[PDB]
Image (cartoon, rainbow, N blue to C red; front, side, top):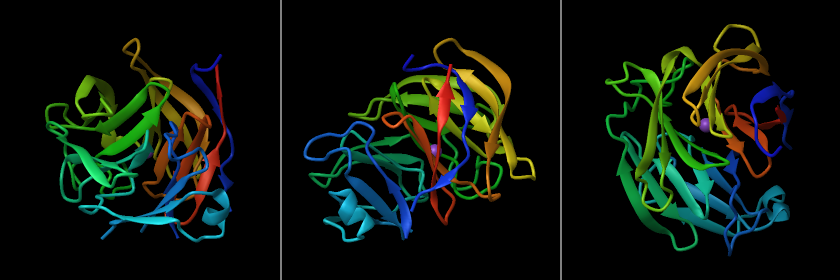
Length: 249
Ligand code: NA
């Protein structure tokens, strides 16, 4: 089937100057092979029309954002860059082709700037994510006492269409990502032998503890972007982009 429960994650494979992203819902004038690189005051977004230009690193367009990014936890979705404004709980939708801020949204009650980071720290309080069902934001609040909160976002206007309060402490996991409507978290032990240790199914409200091995090289709050179009995990560890294959039940 197209979707299912995560049962296996492959070994990370290093992909041959900054974190880059592709659109899982490519929208004309862009195509599947359009790439965007965030140069890491993170404010420049470099746009490459072709994979050749991207690998033969010559950009086709440079965007200047109206404000800098809090972190690399941004996504490109349906022609827009969605990101968190520095030193804020504000998510911004920046339409890339028109260079227009189409929407801004305060994530209500969200902690930011070192309140609810992942276990390895950094300004990772708030993460944007994309899956088969659309656009998400992962965060926490004082109301939720540091438990991971997730909200499905309307990609047009950034309204919170639905919110779930999960039963896992955000600061106790190294990372999190959403596949087929299920939130998965990555453990934070000491070895490179991490695990996908928890799942929360937003379709049912059912959560459980898992033991899926997840290879991780550095004790660093990596930028993980699941790409539902490729059905692969993409991750940036401040040094390289890597891809994890997956298998769904
Ligand atoms: Na992420």
